[PDB]
Length: 279
Image (cartoon, rainbow, N blue to C red):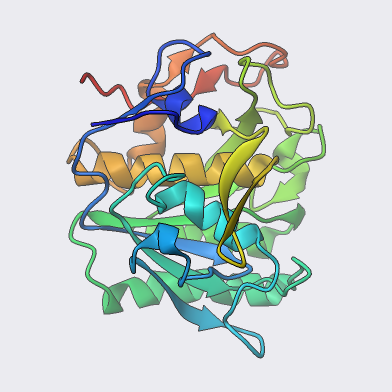
């Protein structure tokens, strides 16, 4: 399948070269998979989600996304126009308030929620969780991410936006999950992207168009935007049967575009997520 005039990041993930604008992908499109977006919520009524999104948990007075960040990330996972895996099921877990903040204890509870809640959902092709959040190093936060991964969920986490080594941030620094840095449309490391040996992969993160609250759209930047490209890619590849939740990060690294990014510090992987789809 071909989506013309796609957002640059979608085109990038199906291309061996920057500078194109059509996204190519297998029509299975993540059908039968599920992606949890652990964030500020999801505006599930947005026409872009086509009834495939729903809120399953909140720790606050509402499950609605009063911020936009979670809706934007969910759109990159699975919206019809802005999403990688256009037929996946999206489940929102609101661990962040409408200012985008959340206590680590709430975030940990949300991860353990997903590890159990997947047993209440129909996801025959597998389960992914996208975590566009983080703060300073915490062994408890890393352990919660490790448990979620161990339970059979492909965990993708943002590297962070500090232009610093991600070893000092959580859950970015947890070895067993997939830690995602950000790149721009010219294949440069995004100016804010964290780096370091703990990164597994880069995805598009600068000037990413996606859904927003109020039934709208906007372009924003962050490792928060790169993470859902990788989460959606995992769901898509799991639906194709090419990999599993336990092996998808490694498979994405195996099949990535290699050596094509600029300003990658010595010791950080030079790997850009790629779907290897042959139309």
